[PDB]
Structures are given as structure tokens and as C-alpha cells.
Length: 310
Length: 310
Image 1 (cartoon, one colour):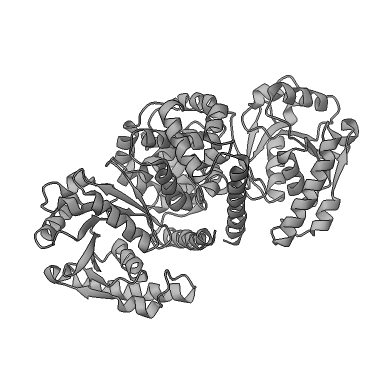
Image 2: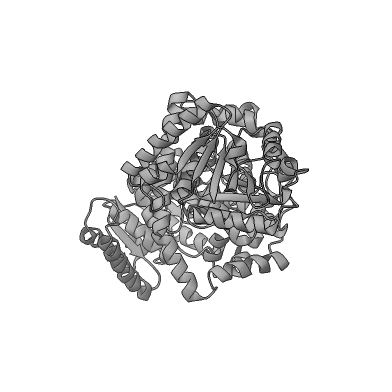
């Protein structure tokens, strides 16, 4: 009934805090001990920060949650009595395959072997493993403590039970899992994100709007509805139902989409134009980027709270 | 220095409340008196509702704001001493052209003639008018009291001063105007919205994700960041700057975009599949749709407040 996190980087530390908030004993493993020590320190500091701002998840005190998180340096002993293993190493296929092969030789048939991968496909990650039926990608969105989405992507041989158990586990810790029925490049979130970026890029390239104003169209406009309702339900409510929306605007949608240009090269003059505008707002140095990310994360923290209330 | 709103429908009543919150005397005109009376009643009730929830814009009391809004049934007398005229009639080209032609024969050279149109192009709306240099589209997003975006779309002959004055006026009343440099079908917001819908539609059609889960990917994922930061700045912060993001992910972006299917027909099996899922969540009847819209608007109201605080 315990949880094992392989890799004590940012993504791993975030998972540790999420599972502990759900009352699960968490084992934090990493090949570098110096990194596990740092992880426990970081986790303690963040837990304290959340406590002081009344932003802790669940009903357990910060102290109790912290006591549930421990370090282990022995993988064989790390998988003992564990029901879910979340792999959190770099986005390097060779490395992930090595770790899953190592886990494959020591785990039982119950435990779920889950990867945090944001891009690697299950077929490339798990094919050939004896425990492939227990394998799955459970991709979180940074920052996971505030953004609940978890994309569950299965391998063609992943069992329904593996998906169901993981969906239930993610819901149990307060996250919002979704079932990506078939693996696909970019899963779902990045495909939608890239669709937006592609058109945004061309609008800037064509001189329709400045990069800064384009972003405002989203942050002070379309994006506000999307923080609460998806694109389909949005259509449903902006007319007398989905059928009504398609009846009223399908002609216009097809007309506009037909006018879309080609796939961007994401370079040259336009990248320089977009970059210059982005840097004017946020200098591209470690300090300014970190400060802006801090602001962004605070907004998300407050939004998550508001979402839960509504 | 006063403002005239032509049309007392929902969009017109919203503009009236926005301008009054900025201290402007507002004249509310409509061809139907029975509709002006209803408008003033609706405005009073909404103003009271906002007051009771501490959601009023600006620093003026609800009472003072209401006293600034009056009705007029004589257009000739309605344009007297007015600096901005916001047209708020149905999205019918013939009707809008008629109204602008009527205004064109009685206004001076200072007043800005602005249309609320969500789709009609300035070239179709204003060409031939003697005061075309003062014409512009200032498209608000429903609900305007909570969503600040205003798309300013000019006619090729619109003067820079007209755009500048309108941009300043919109900022003065607390809105977030953007300069759409050249008119284009769907302006900016709908082009981005349709880009998302197109890919979302295909993902559902291809069986990658259920309609409900697709919406969750946005509402509990990508959409949360978009309520605060646009798609370009989002890229900027998700790497060590825009150049860094394009260096790390441009290859993947192009690869994913290349796999995008054809433009949807927005009908047949998929519309039925999407509609059935939407109706399961929100029955397509006047009562359930209104209730959900009420919930949506409350979320936006609370989000607007949070955005202002951050």
C-alpha cells in the first residue's frame, strides 16, 4: 500500500508531496544520496511554506505528511509492499528503459509501474517487459501541486485494471486523471498547446497582432473560460447546446480554418520578433525567469483553491 | 465626454455598466422603448447584485453609477456632447450599416463610432461613410464585466488617433484592449479558439480521448496557465526563454503539427458523440444551460478579482 518514487528531482519531489497528502507512505529513491538528502530538505521547506499559507492538500498536518516520506537507497528493498512506482528520471529513453528493466526483474504482478514522461511513448518505454500489463505513463503537469491534470497513457498491452487502479489512485490523491485511450505523439495536452502556438505564431508573423497583445487575447480573454471549462463544453454553453453551436458557427469555423497558413519553422525573423517581445516583458536571465515563474505558480496556487471552492 | 450605447440588449447593458463604473455619463438608446425600460431595470438589479457581493468595478457607489445611466429615444439628441458611440445591435450586416449610416449624418469629427461586432469586418461595416476615419470595431467578450479583453479592429482608413483614443478609453474603464493591426476573419480570439476546437474535434473522432476527458485536459490542465499567461510567454517560461523553448521543442512541435488531420465537417457521428457527452454533463434545455452559465460566470467573476489582486 506504499508508494515508491524513483528519482528525487523536481517532478519526483512533487509526486512525493502529493502521495503523502493522501496518507500514503512514500519511499524516495535516487542513485545519488547527496540528491536524496537535498530532496528531503526541499520537501520539508516546501511543506512548511504551504502550511504557512494554508495551501496544504488533504486533511493531514504538514508534520504527519513529512513523517510519511522517507529515503531508500536499495531498490530491491524499495519495492517491498509497494503498490505504485512512479518513475521520475530525465526524459531520456535509454535511461528510462534501463530503470524499467531493473524494476521488471524485482516487482510482483500487483504493483503498477508508472512513468512521468511528457513525450516518450509507452510502446517505446515498456515493450518487452515481463510486467508490461502493469505499465503505464502517468504524466503530471508542472506545477503538479496546483495543476491536477494527469494524462494516463497506456501501452497496447496495458491491462484495464492497471488503468482503472491508477485512475482511482490519482483521484484519491486529489488529482484529475484522464484516460488517453491510445498512445499518440504529444498525448493530448501538448497537441492542443501546439495547435494554439502554431496559429499564434502565424498571426504574429503576418502582422495581425503584436506578441504581447496576442498573449493578452488569451490571458485576459479566452484563457479565463478555459481555467474552468474545456473547449467543447465552452461551445455547448455559448449557444443553445453543441448542436446549436455547430449550426450557428460551423460554416465560419471551416472558413477560418481553411485560411490557416503552413506549419511554422519556429526560427528566423519571427522567433527573433517573438523573443524580443518576451524578453521586454521578462528578461531571459535566471533571476527574472525564476521570479516570473514564482508569480505564475502563486497565481496557479490561488486558482486551484478557487477551483476547489467552485 | 459622455458615452452613447445604441442597443439595449445584453451586450449594450454590459457596456453601460462598464462606462458608468468609469464615471462616464451613459445614454442608453434603443428603437424599442419597452426594451429601454427593461434594460434600466436589468441594469439596476445587476448593479445591486454586484454591490451585495462586493463585485462592483471602480470607486463609485452603485447608486452614483446608476444615476449616470439614462435613456434617450432621440438619436439626434443622443449624440450631443458624446465622445464615444458603441453600437450594440444584432450581428446583421444590413442593420449595422443602416445604423452607422444614420450616425454618419449627425455626428461631428471627434466622436468615435465603434461596433461591438464579433465577426463582421470593418471594411464591410464602414466603407463609404464620411466619418470612416472615426470608425472601429471594439469587440468585447461575454461576460464583459468579468472578461476584460476588447479586440480593437480598424478599417483600413481608421486614423491612428481613433485607435489610440479607444485604446486609452478601454483602459480607463478597466478593460484590456488589444490592437488587431489588420482586419481578419475571426479577428484573434476566434482564430485561436477555432484552432483548439479543430484539433480537439479530431482527437475525439480518432478515439484518443473522450469529450469529457478532453475538456478536463484544458480545465484542470493547460487552461489554468492560460488564465494568467498567454501561449507565447508560456513557452518563454517553460524553458530558459523563447529561444531555449524553440531549441528544445521546435522539432517535436513540427512533428506533431505535421500529423494533424483535415478540417472537421463538424457534423455526423462526431457531433452526435460530442453532443451526447456534453448533454450528459449539462442537459441542453434552457434551465440547465442557464444554470451552468451562471456557475461559469461566477467562476469568472472570482477569477477576475484574483487576477486584479495578482
